[PDB]
Amino acid sequence: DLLKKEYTGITYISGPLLFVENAKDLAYGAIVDIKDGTGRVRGGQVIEVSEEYAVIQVFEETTGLDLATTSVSLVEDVARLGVSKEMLGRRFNGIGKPIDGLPPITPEKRLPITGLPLNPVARRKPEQFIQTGISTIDVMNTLVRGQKLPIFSGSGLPANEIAAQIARQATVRPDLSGEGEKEEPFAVVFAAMGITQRELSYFIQEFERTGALSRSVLFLNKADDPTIERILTPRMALTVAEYLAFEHDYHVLVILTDMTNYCEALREIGAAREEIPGRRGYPGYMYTDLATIYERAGVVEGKKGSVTQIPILSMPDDDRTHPIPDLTGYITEGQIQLSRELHRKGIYPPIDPLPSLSRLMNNGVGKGKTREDHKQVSDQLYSAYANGVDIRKLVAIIGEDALTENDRRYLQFADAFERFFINQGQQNRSIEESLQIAWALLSMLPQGELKRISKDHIGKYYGQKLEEIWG
Amino acid sequence: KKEYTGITYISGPLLFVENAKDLAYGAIVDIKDGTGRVRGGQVIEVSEEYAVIQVFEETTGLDLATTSVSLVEDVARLGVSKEMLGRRFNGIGKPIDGLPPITPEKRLPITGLPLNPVARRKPEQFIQTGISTIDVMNTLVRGQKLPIFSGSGLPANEIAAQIARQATVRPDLSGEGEKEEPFAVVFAAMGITQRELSYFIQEFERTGALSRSVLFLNKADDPTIERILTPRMALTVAEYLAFEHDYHVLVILTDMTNYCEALREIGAAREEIPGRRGYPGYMYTDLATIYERAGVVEGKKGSVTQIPILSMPDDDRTHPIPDLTGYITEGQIQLSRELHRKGIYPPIDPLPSLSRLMNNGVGKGKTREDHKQVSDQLYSAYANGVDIRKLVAIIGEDALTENDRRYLQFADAFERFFINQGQQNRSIEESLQIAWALLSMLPQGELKRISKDHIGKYYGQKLEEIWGAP
Amino acid sequence: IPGIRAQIRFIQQVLEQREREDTFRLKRIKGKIEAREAEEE
Amino acid sequence: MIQGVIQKIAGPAVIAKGMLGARMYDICKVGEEGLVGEIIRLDGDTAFVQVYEDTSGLKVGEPVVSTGLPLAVELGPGMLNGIYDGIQRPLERIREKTGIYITRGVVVHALDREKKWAWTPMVKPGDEVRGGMVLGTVPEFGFTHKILVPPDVRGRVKEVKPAGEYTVEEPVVVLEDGTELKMYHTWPVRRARPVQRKLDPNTPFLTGMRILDVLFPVAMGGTAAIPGPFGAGKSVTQQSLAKWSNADVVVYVGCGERGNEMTDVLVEFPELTDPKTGGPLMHRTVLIANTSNMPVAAREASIYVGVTIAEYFRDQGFSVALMADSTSRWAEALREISSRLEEMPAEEGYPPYLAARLAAFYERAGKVITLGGEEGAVTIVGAVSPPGGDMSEPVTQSTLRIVGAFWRLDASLAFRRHFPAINWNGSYSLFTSALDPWYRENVAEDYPELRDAISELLQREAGLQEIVQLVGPDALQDAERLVIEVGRIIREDFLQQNAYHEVDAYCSMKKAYGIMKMILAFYKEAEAAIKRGVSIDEILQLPVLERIGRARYVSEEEFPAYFEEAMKEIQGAFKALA
Amino acid sequence: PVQRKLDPNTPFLTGMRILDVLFPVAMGGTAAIPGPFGAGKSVTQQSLAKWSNADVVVYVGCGERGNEMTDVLVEFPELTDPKTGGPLMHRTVLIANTSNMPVAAREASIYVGVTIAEYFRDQGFSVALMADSTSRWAEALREISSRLEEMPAEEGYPPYLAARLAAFYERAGKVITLGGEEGAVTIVGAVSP
Amino acid sequence: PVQRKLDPNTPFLTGMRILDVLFPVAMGGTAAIPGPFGAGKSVTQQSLAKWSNADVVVYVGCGERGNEMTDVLVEFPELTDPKTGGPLMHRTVLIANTSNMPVAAREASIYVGVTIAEYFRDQGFSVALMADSTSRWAEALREISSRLEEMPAEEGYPPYLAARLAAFYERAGKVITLGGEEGAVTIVGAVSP
Ligand SMILES: Nc1ncnc2c1ncn2[C@@H]1O[C@H](COP(=O)(O)OP(=O)(O)OP(O)(O)=S)[C@@H](O)[C@H]1O
Ligand SMILES: Nc1ncnc2c1ncn2[C@@H]1O[C@H](COP(=O)(O)OP(=O)(O)OP(O)(O)=S)[C@@H](O)[C@H]1O
Ligand SMILES: Nc1ncnc2c1ncn2[C@@H]1O[C@H](COP(=O)(O)OP(=O)(O)O)[C@@H](O)[C@H]1O
Ligand SMILES: [Mg+2]
Ligand SMILES: [Mg+2]
């Protein structure tokens, strides 16, 4: 256990891979230490082992390695991370080593970083509504506790600002749910993969201003850090998140800052191994690999805690059909998609609701949870906005003056929707504020055209004007 | 019988047997295992070291210790006879109708020899399919390859069955009166489901059309090598009947898209690098070796006529399968989804359809003196009716000229009565009468493609064949 | 119409390029199958 | 037994050496933990094993033992209420044995060996029995579970246990020559269970959705596919079918999908009621759960286990619905295994035999005369998840060629929140003609004509949309604009169906017939009024349009009165308003 | 080999006013013709074979349909030669390949035909060479390239398709033969996109 | 190495109205200017070199025309440094690897330029680094990868292309140097899609 064994006789070094022979007693998936002639020790993992030779992916760069002096020594048979409640105020790199200057964590447990799949029988149904303060999320794409709700972004779009705002404003509403009790705030696990200095500084400063660093675990892999550490980074972050949530009753919010970089590292490793790729050269096991990360969120029966994931990915050319967003949407419960057209209009947050989706929205809204009209109001808003968009496309042909008055009303509803319901800035809107804004918007349309709303809700809420809400 | 023990490799559909230098390439072998079960297989590669055998069925249960391989025949051969009429086969010539195996008059290699181009002759006589949109406008000529271009949900199987049980020759129109000229239908089904299999069996048995038909029915879960061999068996039987017993043979091949997919999969299994669009680079040649076996031969009274049926994958005619089929065959009959969803059967659209050999098999002494001109006038008038139907939606009914309204009425009645045949069996005279009744809706002298003689002889009748007097 | 035609030809070129890349990868893996079978025997 | 050692480990793939005599597709125990794997290649003295569990931590040299048998499922009483993994392991027992996480190497019987069953024999000594014959009956949840002879067992009954309580391991019937028949038997999941003959698809499979049960029906023994991009509503449609179908038994296979959906089924279903039995809905449902983060090699096993269980329940005379929640995940698993095998792909990475495997899976459906003489059916509805929504993908194209119904979803309607979001233009069904006699006998004699008229209206609307997108809807004449308006009325209050509304979630055939009759009566009257000079904008203001729109929210019990009132209102409104 | 290639300064007279006047081809030039279905391509080809000032006509059927090849093989032996009254086939060489004949023959058909044309040119004759479909020949070339596992260039065609077409068409020309006598080969190649 | 990375709070004044007004870049920031040929990437780079407020300008001619490097070498000595008033060339360091120079040296030239810029940053200067085209560096990486028989990721580029680009662009930024002074590197990298 604690005696050292070293394998010399490296036979091949190229890119991220390393071949060592006569290593038949290295376990598959084992973590190894690569020592060079200068005494520096690198990290590595066994990705294929046979009685001839073992294949090791090197986490750091391979500069300075040589077949005559390099030595590979086993660290542990299974990649494990030492976890404790002590690391709630700590910062770590992509491989879990401290970078904040404090001494290393004294672990209570050492857990496998790949985790284990949750038994579907042991899961709960995620039902507790989370108020993010953003109307296009609260009303139309409701986020519930224990959901995987990624943000589909672009190169210039402000997904980081939206994630920071959600982390700042997210709260449950026990008074609406009938629990009526004080609630502890979210613990935040922030996994950054290939993050630039600008985004990192923004996130650090936001968490400092909001005072959430003292309850936030940070795994930071910089853009100039080695890219193979990005494979370990989200698994370690989610190991910490699962430990906290399901063994200390923490409600954990997990932010994975860029899954596109994770998929880039995965593609690099797969191509080095000549894996049979899927579309656009990404490995065929990318769906399973992303699933082993996303499916670690949720709520478990008999447990107080929860894990909520908000991954962030940038669709390369705003292409929703790209393999990364496609597989992510196939795995997660819906997505929040940003619109470049809304961003260019100056609307923040630039969330367009039509391509967005929340699959667990039905679980958390309705009577006794938020309000009786939530679902029908959301459906009516979607229908009216789609009508407005179609009428915009029609205007692009026949011109505005050739419209009827009802199409004109839908066009006015569409642009008022964009400029008032979506465009909200940094203000924190309660669900009641968002609902009254939505009803004021719906009051622009004829009463009989709210076909998706029951007459009771229409009688109770229809009539208010936007200028009555704010001067 | 020599048994080749020494299996050294099993993976997917392939197995390697050593010391098999005596196995000829392409031979069919029997694979026996510890349980005594026998599977079929084909030698796809033979060398000094080992022979590569592609197993027909799944390789489950095989092991390198107890598996044995033995030869059954060095060349894929089919035993053909005239008693094949009224029988059903599973795509490799094994009966599946419960009747005893036929006594083979002779055994023929299913990889048929190519017809000598100087031995062929021009197709000159037609086949009466009983369908007006084919008989009148896209006439099928004895010796033609006239594919049907179908879609995902279109009733191509129903049309295939109807043609199979309605197609006949008309020697009385040529003046021969020779009913002694036999007619047979060879029906090859590839990659069909149990539903389609039951439908085809019921259709062939209920009308008695089975007695002049040979069925090679390959199911969707049958081995893909059987799918590849099925059209070879069907065309071997067709060639035998036509050029050794003077039969007039109609061969219906459904579905060629399934055959192309099976060819793609088998090429991938043999580690061949695919060509254009992911299909094998030799798909053109394979489809040619299938299609070009139809024809009429100088000095022989028989004929082979082919009606391939293929579903365009995304209703795309640029797809490799319909594209190469158009390269090889003489025209196409295109089914229409908009006609189908309007309730018209058969949903054959005359405008994109085309029979390239039609003008050789119609006219005086073959069908009737007015056939070609009637077809041309019908085509032009229907095109005018369709575009006026599009225009009337914006400009309104009354804004059109009177003859434009007449074209509207003609197009509506054409779709109602000519195309919408139903399960009727219409002789070419009935179809021509219906066409003339429809053309009588247009004013005399508007029929510009038709000579004045035919107009005087046939113009004037009104629509009574279908409504008022069926 | 010209814009749609240009878009069609652009999409066709992209699809053909992806097919060419797939064929190149298939050639590489077939060569590696043959080589790794040949030397190992 | 064949014993060897591990030679190479690479992900889910383990190569063993010393496995001479091992057979293809036999189950092996890999490592000292005895992980379940399957042999997919034999090469010299080696065997290629795809492990159905996680291989992390395995070392070269660990033993590999072949069991000499392919993957098999235990078929007997005890499956009608449980949830299983890919290789038929009960997840309740696994949870009780391991906790909130699924650990590899857990061995547990598929059927509870201690549960007692009320046995009632149907045979006497001296009787000769063939495969598939009913030895006796056992009650499970109001179902009369029939104990069947294994399909390839023949003999004469020598001794039969009298009526009483026994476990599934008890040999209730002992044949001559000493062969013992228990309450359960094992069957290889890759072998189709034999039948006497396949029957024609006479009766329909009532899904409870108006668009699927009217425009694109599937027969009781047919096959359907529902492909669409993510968010289109594949799983909601699958769960609606599982809740509202007229099938006796529902087998739901979550092949490579979200675990939260399996949890949703596990929580909601016990509270819902079976429409025909009256008991809890979960009592007629069998779940085979293989979530996306569970081992990849087990997805194929999951599909085969589900279809084999469906076949077994069919052999008892039941009408079984099999919902495979994704076959694209099975295809991706095959591609991953092929990549580990270093085999040349066919198209987009998938192995050449993918189409053959899909065809074999889909051909197991059908209405059949079982070996016991009784009549049962299996209906397979398979979801497809094309990458990027590209319907030209090989899995979707391979599925097009073997299914009788095709329910195509489009993201355009899902974005609009128009549900079920079936693309009418891209969908079809090959069962419309064969089901017409049943519709005439059971719904209305004029139902096929009414459905054809609705389809023709939708076709006309589709044709006119080409001009609407060109010059706008106001450039049309009154008749064509009326067709457009009637088309959108159809789409909004006949094709839409709220799967969460307490009334709209289900719709009987007669309610859909009434809605169609109302819509077409309105259309005929509106066209007649158009011909007499009434404006279309005047027609669109009739409150009877509001009645038509609200028709779908009317309960089944009170619908006939609403329908008669609305027909009277249609006639009166278009008599008074000319 | 030839002694010298001459200038395209004398005309190849097809006997058709539109081609001879508006779109002429020099003696030894090359022309391409698309083949729409009903556009009467066969009649034009027969007119070139029958009325042009070429002494010998070489007709190459590369990959034609069975019935389309049968049309030619049946109807050329009926054409009478205006210059002699006798059959036109008495100064015609026919190369006929159908789609089901081996791909190597279909690929070598144009080379065989043009080599025969060059041989008759070396005797001082003027030869008109007609390639009935170079698209079918290109399909055969693509199939052979695929069988050799070569890289597909554009639309699956081998990257040397243009080189092969140029090598085929450059064989045409009016030359001084090695015997010191003037001869020419004029190529009219049909394309079917 | 540096002591600390600072937030960029001062603008990189390029002298071009559209860039300095509508799309400003900060002193430690990074900017990409992709465009087709003839769009004016190099003109913008040279305008930045002539007119920007950087203490030192490092211009990297990665795989582009030699005439542009000659133009810089000839014109810059005559121009005036906008900050100090001396000759503009004393402010400038040129790393030139023209298109017909060895391809493998493009990758080396990029790193040499960025390292020299970082060295001048360490002395307390603000440095503008102009990369004439990173697409040529990517093409050099593709060629070397093809020689290595590595499996290409997308359009033939190696899968680690994004990693190299990220590591190159991450070297820019406003920092407190190890000596305690404040320096910055601004990178403007042209792309040639
Ligand atoms: N110059 C012409 N003079 C008279 N009739 C012509 C002429 N060109 C074509 N035709 C007519 O066209 C028919 C014969 O040529 P076509 O069949 O049209 O040739 P083709 O079908 O285009 O040949 P392909 O494309 O290789 S199948 C006969 O009806 C001729 O009368
Ligand atoms: N700002 C400008 N003011 C004046 N002329 C300009 C300007 N930008 C570009 N041009 C002109 O356009 C030409 C193109 O120059 P560049 O923009 O440097 O070309 P490029 O972007 O480097 O693309 P290439 O040719 O592939 S290097 C210049 O030579 C000038 O003639
Ligand atoms: N028939 C329906 N009725 C109401 N809402 C639906 C319906 N189908 C889908 N939805 C909504 O759309 C979301 C996406 O559907 P879902 O089935 O989860 O996606 P997928 O197509 O991948 O299975 C659901 O979570 C639900 O909110
Ligand atoms: Mg789903
Ligand atoms: Mg430049």
Image (tube, coloured by chain):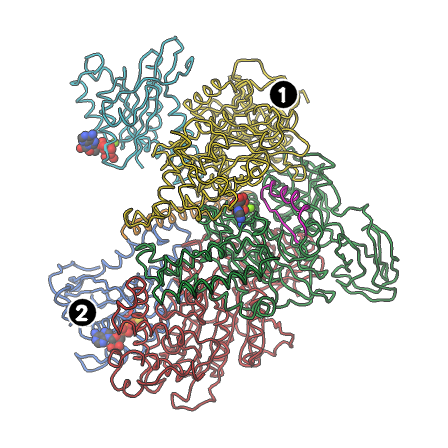
Chain colours: A yellow, B red, C orange, D green, E blue, F cyan
Sort mark 2 into few (<14), some (14-19) or many (20+) by Cα contacts within 10 Å: some
What's the residue at 78%, 65% (across, down)? Answer: D130
Q: Quadrant of residue B336?
A: bottom left
Q: Is residue A383 magenta?
A: no
Specify whether tag 1 is near ligand 3 (CB below 8 Å): no
Residue E69 % position (x, y): 33, 72
What's the residue at 33%, 77% (across, down)? Answer: B375
Q: Which of the numbered marks, if any, corresponds to residue B253? A: none
The quadrant of the rendered image in which ligand 5 is seen is top left
Q: Chain of mark 1?
A: A
Q: Chain of mark 2?
A: E
Q: Residue furthest front?
A: D576
Q: Is residue D6 above or below residue D561?
A: above
Magenta-colored span: D250-273
- Marks 2/1 in contact by CB < 8 Å: the verdict is no
Residue D301 % position (x, y): 64, 48
Which secondary structure, mark 2?
loop
Which is closer to the viewer, label 2 or label 1? Answer: 1
Q: Is residue E93 visible?
A: no
Q: Is residue F127 above or below residue A426?
A: above
Q: Quadrant of residue F165?
A: top left
Point out the image quarter for the N terminus of chain A. top right
The one nearer the camera, B342 or A332, is: B342
Which secondary structure, mark 1?
loop
Q: Is residue D16 above or below residue B316?
A: above
Residue A327 % position (x, y): 50, 41
Sort mark 1 into few (<14), some (14-19) or many (20+) by Cα contacts within 10 Å: some
Q: Amino acid at mark 1?
A: Ser
Q: Which of the numbered marks, if any, corresponds to residue E125? A: 2
Residue D73 % position (x, y): 71, 51
The one nearer the camera, A388 or B126, is: A388
Q: Which of the numbered marks, if any, corresponds to residue A84? A: 1
